[PDB]
Length: 266
Figure 1 (cartoon, rainbow, N blue to C red):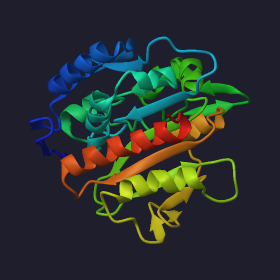
Figure 2: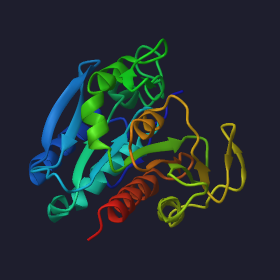
Figure 3: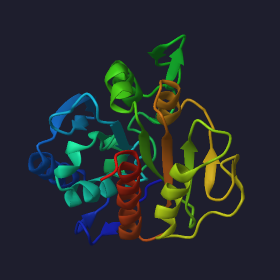
């Protein structure tokens, strides 16, 4: 249940949520990002950070992390990604970020929130209308209440940064409007592949992984919801939890760089 690692990049425990929000505030402030508290989970804010001066003709990319509290390299990786950003990047992309969706899970190093709910499932779209259902977590309900904002924010792409806690090898879930995976899928999986071995062909969580990619597999996940809502492409990256935290942190940041690089090129 509880998973905790030490980060040397951040000189703290992976569950150090006070340190997390402190460093996230520093980056928000450095880059001039707008901060919007979508809601609170266990008196911890669920933020939507948006780059400044978002223009009509630039792609709208959304990056999300921390749906599952044990998959801590997502949020820390996002923090690492931001820390390397220049600000010039925002001249070519309207970047939005959900840095931590499950703070109560994150703070304790466990998958579910304090209520035992899975925040990554129960996102529905019924005859064009976004809505929660019987299995939506409190956080999921908070995000669904700002469905329009998040759909606009991810119009040109969604990247959610997960970890498969008991895996040693890496893989990606991708969504593209084609019969087979393309450059988009391959570049993101290659980015993770620079850090870890790619998962061999077979069933990972009852899904077929072919050449490091599970392609167009829809369920009630946040990324499935945003792709069905109109996001051009999608990715749910899966860094392996049995690897060292800092390597997973770097791999996550690397995938975010590749994601933004492809969809909003220099």
